Length: 129
Image 1 (cartoon, rainbow, N blue to C red):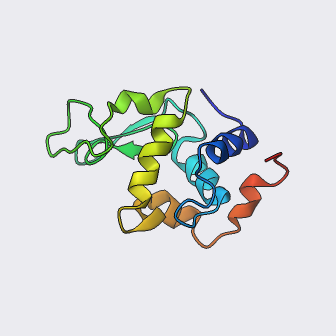
Image 2 (cartoon, rainbow, N blue to C red):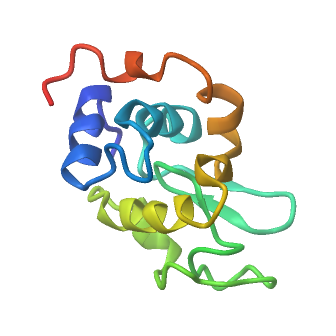
């Protein structure tokens, strides 16, 4: 599914992401924009052989099982394919665990490079929330 901007903001807020570990909703929308362009089916291979899955590009090196990442853990206890569902529940839950891991949203390199320090409220402007 490719979410609309406000549509995704609403879903993330219903799933408890808004202000989770102190990160306003705009931070999460912005991350998703640059990770996946709001597409739950996005996948991308990393240099190390792991793969990133879903709207928040969660990686198989640590967080999900894809059967093909030798280093690996599955700390979210989830097949990576669950992260590609129309229903964002598994991506949200696993993102809550990642953002709690010590480095906050820095775990998403794209968030650090493209969202951190910017006016992330713009990403939820105009949305009924």
